[PDB]
Image (spheres, helix red, strand yellow):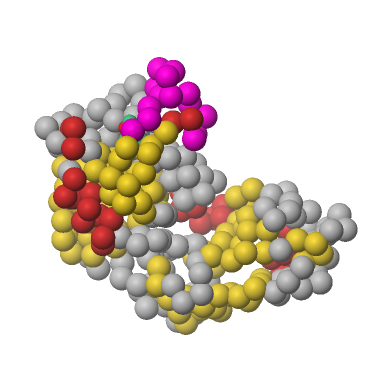
Amino acid sequence: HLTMPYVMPGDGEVVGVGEPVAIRFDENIADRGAAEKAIKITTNPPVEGAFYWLNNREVRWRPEHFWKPGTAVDVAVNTYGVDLGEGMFGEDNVQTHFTIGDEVIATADDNTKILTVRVNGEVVKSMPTSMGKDSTPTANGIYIVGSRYKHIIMDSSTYGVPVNSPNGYRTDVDWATQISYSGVFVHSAPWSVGAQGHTNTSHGCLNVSPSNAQWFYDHVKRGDIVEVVNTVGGTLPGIDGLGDWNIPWDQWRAGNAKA
Ligand SMILES: *SC1C=CC(OC)C=C1
């Protein structure tokens, strides 16, 4: 009947302007309100933020707008002995201190088929891309950068689609940067370098050149932003895991502490 929290990002990390604070618990939290009250977030410079739950075990906190570069963030999860409902008690306190690095925002525009990277306002890179083909389009929205992989075997069964079923796949991929928990990545796509900038051919990922994918791997960090615009797809869910910013501030602020 004890639940331990885990906070992200990790102590000492430098993260991009889209990185929310994340407190994950190893058990469903009955009393979200108690959990929220136990978590103190301090920022310098000070900015307003708010909690919103992505599922029964993980709550997120972020501001209305992307963080200002340079901001220092302190999180104290003071859950030791707190009654979190249905007879579950916080097993422990946890903490983290982190800082916000440079503003890196990349936009993938399906009308141009170009992924442009802006660092602190200025364009530093302009990569042709090939996104989701019309029958499996890439969703528009704001994506937060997660993990990066030098090499990875991309397998659709990970995400509930059998490899040998119509939209299935299993492929070795290089220089992959994760941007949704649903399995969207910016990655090396040596096969479609002729289609990149012209035609969408993917299952939903952002195909770029091997060298552009390596650059993206090397120069993006956790919490940087990728925005996809003008596709024929839907909208990344706000509760994806990396889709937090697609929930409008009015709704995020109001929260969901009583659900
Ligand atoms: S992210 C991704 C998904 C499928 C691929 O090719 C089968 C490549 C990348």
Above or below, 141 against 91 in this view is: above
Determine the residue positioned at 47% across, 51% down: 242
**Numbered range of the magenta stretch:** 158-171
Residue 248 at x, y percent in the picture: 49, 52
Above or below, 150 against 95 in this view is: above
Residue lying at the far left of the rendered structure:
194
Q: Is residue 82 left or right of residue 123?
A: right
Determine the residue positioned at 48% across, 30% down: 157
Q: How many marks?
A: 0
Q: Main secondary structure of the magenta part?
A: loop
Residue 201 at x, y percent in the picture: 25, 28
Q: Quadrant of ligand 1?
A: top left
Q: Work out whether residue 246 or residue 203 is closer to the camera in this orientation and state it.
A: 203
Residue 210 at x, y percent in the picture: 19, 45
Determine the residue positioned at 77% across, 68% down: 91
Above or below, 12 against 250 in this view is: below
